[PDB]
Amino acid sequence: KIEEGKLVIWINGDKGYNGLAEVGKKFEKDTGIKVTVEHPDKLEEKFPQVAATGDGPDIIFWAHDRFGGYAQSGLLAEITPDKAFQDKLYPFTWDAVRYNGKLIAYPIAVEALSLIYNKDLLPNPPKTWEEIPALDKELKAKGKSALMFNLQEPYFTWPLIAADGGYAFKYENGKYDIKDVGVDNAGAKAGLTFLVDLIKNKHMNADTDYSIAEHAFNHGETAMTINGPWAWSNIDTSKVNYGVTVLPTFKGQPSKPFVGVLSAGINAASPNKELAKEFLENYLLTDEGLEAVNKDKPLGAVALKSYEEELAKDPRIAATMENAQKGEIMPNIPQMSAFWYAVRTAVINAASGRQTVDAALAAAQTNAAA
Amino acid sequence: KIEEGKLVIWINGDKGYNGLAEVGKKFEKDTGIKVTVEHPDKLEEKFPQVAATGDGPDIIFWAHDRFGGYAQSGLLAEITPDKAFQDKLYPFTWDAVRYNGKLIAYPIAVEALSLIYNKDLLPNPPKTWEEIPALDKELKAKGKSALMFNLQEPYFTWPLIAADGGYAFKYENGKYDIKDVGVDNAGAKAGLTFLVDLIKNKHMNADTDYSIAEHAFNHGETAMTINGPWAWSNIDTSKVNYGVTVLPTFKGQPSKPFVGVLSAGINAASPNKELAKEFLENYLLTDEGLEAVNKDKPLGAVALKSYEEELAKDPRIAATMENAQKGEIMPNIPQMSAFWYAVRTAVINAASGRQTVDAALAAAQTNAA
Ligand SMILES: OC[C@H]1O[C@H](O[C@H]2[C@H](O)[C@@H](O)[C@@H](O)O[C@@H]2CO)[C@H](O)[C@@H](O)[C@@H]1O
Ligand SMILES: OC[C@H]1O[C@H](O[C@H]2[C@H](O)[C@@H](O)[C@@H](O)O[C@@H]2CO)[C@H](O)[C@@H](O)[C@@H]1O
Ligand SMILES: [Cl-]
Ligand SMILES: [Cu+2]
Ligand SMILES: [Cu+2]
């Protein structure tokens, strides 16, 4: 079970958990309540397992797409901000955390992937995916590469897969049709085929993951990476002269990243719901609370209107929002976990050459629709 | 082709490359010759590909096991230390880089994996692999795990596989029989099966890699990890109260890590062979040079006698040598790269459940021979 009189928070290890811990220290200084911030592996998978038994964190942070599943499984407390508090956050961010008519988490920030590039190696970033092999040929001659990014998580490859027509679930008449999946269509096939060709022609390696790409970019081994706002801090530290910009187009069309709203849900089994509410509304979701987290690892475009307006002039955030507008907000429906698992397998199997692109996506299509 | 009048060095990203760069800056300061230290991805695969076309770095750092393969391909210059310099290093480290009667690299340091444990979480670490499932169950109740280590590179799982009888190439009377491969015998199958069982029982995850394990240990999420001396610097930084100790036994037998001698080879295509020799003999392989590297990322037990003497009181190094004594120094023969590729595939396939242990090891056996 969950311990009373304190708060346990889970957040992913790529986020500003040290900053969040500082907000927690302030909370403790004011209320005497200890806040423990943890970053378990696979937390988005563990949470539903442990929460069902009445254990786990008081508060879970993740992108909003996971939350409908958690809500449908009875794992989340309905949140009860008054109208005054609601007015403090952008309406579209509340939309991301509304499920079956109820608010099931507090929205924190809007995230989208951008192209990040080393201005020393590449003063002019490429407008198109198609020119990346040419850039890589140039750079390979200097002992570098053009582009490295996490190929192990479909989140990162999705923008390209979606560009020419791939989609998750078709929206119609105000709801997602979970039986209409867009993962094995011509557009999705074109996008994944391009990625696989990049690997076949040795411009990328199938096993490149988050840490490998981050290392390479931050040590100037590769001219570009694809990543979210949380990654800017480590780049700052590495002293690389970087820019953040619109993702490359594919077949003349915008890459379409899936947009996540980082959100904080309260465990239905928590005996500290009021403390969790006070922490989130009166400490984290303030100018100063968001600053503490953002200073650790940037959040993106925060849900709090006041602080968002303050940071909006940041060109990196402008780029983030440009990419977000070109993409689509993720659904929060329970079927999303099945979608992501299916596409994850498809990309890994196609990238490694274990399956053809056609075979991989045909299977994912079926798997995603249950 | 390689640029004349400078030095390009490749070394793995887990080593003290910044320390090495400092030795390089000292070289440039004294000679005007710029030294560029790089740490490319998959450099042990990269080097032979580019060196075959006469490009690549002037100097390549890797464990000695890969060097016999490079030499047979003609990718390395024979090196020419006088006897006075050779006597500066331990004969057994020179043995590791002797191929076809010739010295094909400079030995730098001796590496072996040890068990690293969080003293606060686990004051008395387990002596056996067999007690790990019960330890994990107890720690899981506390929100921790018992053990996380890199399951993606067979280097890290080899000690368990070799514990009860597994081996690469039969070594008899001072010679390796490249036809007598021990990767699919009862011992190796017992070892790998125990590993796969840990995963099946959720005590470990098949996808755990170097970064995941390092993060978990250095943030106190797991009580133990398995790693080499290069890892200690990041643990120091993390403030985890750690100890370095003997690997757990399996079926009553010591884990048997493959011991590596970090070594520096000179590209046969380098136009700077003399500069490279100078940098290596007169700058790197000195108490000051090695200290610079070691202070960045610990080297282990260095090949240079004088400096090894000076660091030998370090209990972490003593534990490293105790594990090394229980293991086996790697062969340097050309067949090693085939051996490693085959075993890596087998461990990953068995761990993921894509193939049975028996089938994975049988394929590796065939591929390695
Ligand atoms: O890759 C599938 C994965 O995508 C998204 O996860 C993102 C997350 O939104 C970001 O905040 C960041 O942490 O990177 C993650 C990808 O590694 C979905 O939110 C997640 O449900 C899904 O499994
Ligand atoms: O995993 C196979 C791999 O094992 C050894 O590589 C070690 C290396 O010796 C250490 O210095 C350290 O870098 O970790 C490596 C494992 O990731 C062999 O030397 C290497 O040939 C082999 O592929
Ligand atoms: Cl819907
Ligand atoms: Cu963590
Ligand atoms: Cu590197």
Image (cartoon, coloured by chain):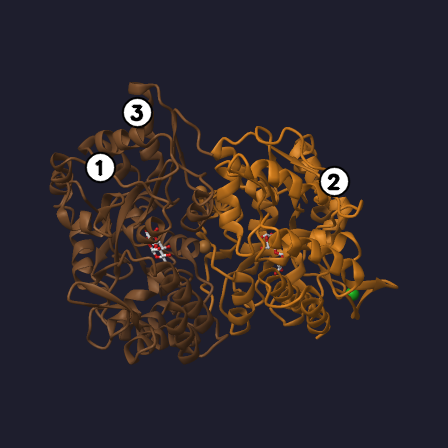
Chain colours: A orange, B brown
In this rendering, would A309 be left or right of A26?
right
Disc 2 under 8 Å from ligand 1? The reply is no
Indicate the position of residue B281 as horizontal and vertical percent values.
22, 33
Q: Residues within 10 Å of mark 2 (few under 14, many from 20)?
A: some
Q: Nearer the viewer, residue B326 or B272?
A: B272
Name the residue at 73% across, 60% down: A331
Q: Residues within 10 Å of mark 1 (few under 14, many from 20)?
A: some
* Cβ atoms under marks 1 and 2 closer than 8 Å: no
Between marks 3 and 1, how big is the CA–CA gap?
20 Å
Going by the numbered disc 3, the residue's amino acid type is: Phe
Residue placed furthest toward the right: A173
Quadrant placement of the C terminus of chain B? bottom left
Subunit under mark 2: A
Q: Is residue A5 above or below residue B6?
A: below
In this rendering, would B89 be left or right of B276?
left
Q: Which residue is mark 2?
A: A322
Badge nearest the viewer, 3 or 1 = 1
Q: Secondary structure at mark 3?
A: helix
**Residue B310 sits in which quadrant?**
top left
Subunit under mark 1: B
Badge nearest the viewer, 2 or 3 = 3
Subunit under mark 3: B
Going by the numbered disc 2, the residue's amino acid type is: Glu
Badge nearest the viewer, 1 or 2 = 1
Indicate the position of residue B114 as horizontal and vertical percent values.
25, 58
**Residue B252 sits in which quadrant?**
bottom left
Going by the numbered disc 1, the residue's amino acid type is: Thr
Q: Is residue A39 above or below residue A113?
A: below
**Residue B132 sits in which quadrant?**
bottom left
Between marks 1 and 2, how big is the CA–CA gap?
60 Å
Q: Which residue is mark 1?
A: B80
Question: Residue B27 got which mark?
Answer: 3
